[PDB]
Image: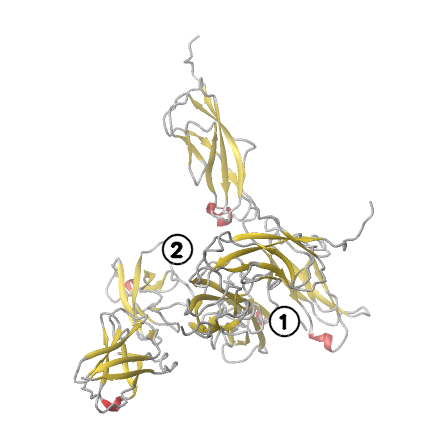
Amino acid sequence: AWITAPVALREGEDLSKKNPIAKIHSDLAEERGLKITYKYTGKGITEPPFGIFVFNKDTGELNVTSILDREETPFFLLTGYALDARGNNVEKPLELRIKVLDINDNEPVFTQDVFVGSVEELSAAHTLVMKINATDADEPNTLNSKISYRIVSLEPAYPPVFYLNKDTGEIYTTSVTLDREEHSSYTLTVEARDGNGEVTDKPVKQAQVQIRILDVNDNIPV
Amino acid sequence: QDVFVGSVEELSAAHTLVMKINATDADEPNTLNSKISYRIVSLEPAYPPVFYLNKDTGEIYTTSVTLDREEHSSYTLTVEARDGNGEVTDKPVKQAQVQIRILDVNDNIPVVENKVLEGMVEENQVNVEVTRIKVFDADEIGSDNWLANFTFASGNEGGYFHIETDAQTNEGIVTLIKEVDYEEMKNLDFSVIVANKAAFHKSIRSKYKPTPIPIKVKVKNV
Amino acid sequence: RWAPIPCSMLENSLGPFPLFLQQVQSDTAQNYTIYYSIRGPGVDQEPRNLFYVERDTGNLYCTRPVDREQYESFEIIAFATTPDGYTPELPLPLIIKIEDENDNYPIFTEETYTFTIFENCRVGTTVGQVCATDKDEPDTMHTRLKYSIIGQVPPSPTLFSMHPTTGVITTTSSQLDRELIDKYQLKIKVQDMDGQYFGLQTTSTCIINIDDVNDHLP
Amino acid sequence: RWAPIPCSMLENSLGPFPLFLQQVQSDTAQNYTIYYSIRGPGVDQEPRNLFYVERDTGNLYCTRPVDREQYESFEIIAFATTPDGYTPELPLPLIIKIEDENDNYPIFT
């Protein structure tokens, strides 16, 4: 006899143009005049989260009603039911699975507001200085969570002094020579980002980087 | 009325009352011809609804979704009155606006920049300043819910020092309350932890545990 | 038993084809060898070949793009058959609806609109009206129109104005001497979706003549 | 934009590296002690540390063999500084030329 499949719904958009998604209803009930009323149990309809699905008590249609969040549930698993007016289960209960599908909807957030570092005077080009770290709420080892780090502001802003490797969050020096006797420190600002990044315009989140220039004995006691 | 007003609080419990609405009919007292009943015309978002209307009694109550004063300072919705029993006429009937002000609670946590502190005092003085901490909170400006309130985590046994929050600024100010002696050259270090001057909401409380901030202090001679 | 679940396809779909609609299996393939087929106005009755099925997994697809313009809904039977030529179980009726977007353009009800107006008629005289129609479902946003002038030939004087909901053209200025300028053209636009950003535009040009009185001296 | 009269290095060079390229300096060297440096692709964008300069005397060099197939020239900014950190002279966009070796194929009409 004929069988049914599972369904899959995406994070973050209005699914009001995708309904109805499933239905629990009897095929011959009508040929005995037999009145049925219908209910679903499960996470999303009788357990959390709330708001997200509704059903028609007479015709057993299942409808989405609010925004899905894959950072709240990646799956749900309902059971639907069919009773007469007294108590009898007219149909055998139906299993219904609902996959949620993930998008990038959260931007990565640093282990610190302001990171601290050190680099020595008179050192060679591309001297490694420090590492900055952040975390993402989408699903690990994927492109919605895959972090890139960049410099957004620098003080003194000229000449150029540092680069940020976008793929690790490590901070390196340029070929310009550093001197403890002139710049006790530096300060710049870093932005963590995710995914492919094209045409983003809603603001994203930032931290500070502060670098101490460590002394060498390059001057004599006159 | 043209427009009805009432009050809900944020984060409330379910099916607790809010307010009544009122209409009037011209037929006879206590008859079904003037036996009024209501509905909610439109609401936004329309599901889950943030309010429930007993349609027979004219009373408005909370649902199983909570309001947020940090989202809206007032919720709007529309109402309609009819009368008698059974199916509704296919003709127009009058409507009016409802507005629910949303009262604020201590779900917003006081947050700071500052994380450790130091300062100085002289001997043979009292009521003199040492240091400060400036505080932010997302609750209403001047409420007991918004006032940062500091208390000791260590060094209280001395009775030497205090921290008082100003309600102008939400800035804690630290002072010397009992006299100190330079000639004993004792340790006067202590530490403080923030809450608010009101407790934290039933669903929100203990979900976080802040750490203390140490203050260190040193004495001058006369 | 439980009855089957409804399905649909959005009109004018880009593809490529075939485009998947549902999986329809039977649990009986577990207890003996069946394969999958479909029948009705949709495969073997006109429209022919529109739906297709995998005879080995019951995946059920469409072969080409449809139109809400042209079609509404379709009833198709699924059934199972053995390789030795017999049908041991009941068939499954399917229900399948076409879904609608605004995607059919508005179009003016004439190849070019013409108008005649008497020399120096008064400001706000009704010059005429431009009508368009739209073949998506009536009284909807998908057929809701918005009417605009976009520009004038000759570009000067400023002489006409258009009513937004109906394309109703009036005059704005009574400098209308035929003996100085005898015809105007107006570059005109109609769009659906209350003329929103996402509504679909069709442009035309309409003509306005200055209809003669006798006033130039022999 | 254009840039000053160039200096060459072949592609596919065999060294010994560092191979030398040029000395461009600042026209008032007698007033202050200068320190001479370089920046741009080839030093501090990619590929990194293809190029170098004598920091005290401004003689320029490169560190490894290069290919010409994606470029006939290289471009970098040379900049002046002092031991007290300040800029005596304005920075100059220079050009290096990459000369050929035969490694493109001959191909019939």
**Residue C170 at x, y = what percent?**
41, 31
Label disc, if present, on residue B90 of the rendered structure: 2
Is D81 placed left or right of A5 in the picture?
Answer: left
Within 10 Å of disc 2 (Cα), the crowding (few <14, some 14-19, many 20+) is: few
What is the quadrant of residue A116 in the picture? bottom left
Residue at point 53%, 38% (across, down): C203
- Residue linked to disc 1: A4
Evaluate whether label 1 is on the same chain as label 2.
no
**Residue C181 at x, y = what percent?**
46, 21
Residue closer to the observer: A158 or B170: A158
What is the quadrant of residue A5 in the picture? bottom right
**Residue A172 at x, y = what percent?**
52, 68
Is D95 placed left or right of A46 in the picture?
Answer: right
The kind of residue on which mark 2 rests is: Asp
Quick one: quadrant of the C terminus of chain D?
top right
Indicate the secondary structure of the residue bearing disc 1.
loop
Give the spatial CA distance, label 1 vs label 2: 42 Å
Is B142 placed left or right of D68 in the picture?
Answer: left
The kind of residue on which mark 1 rests is: Thr
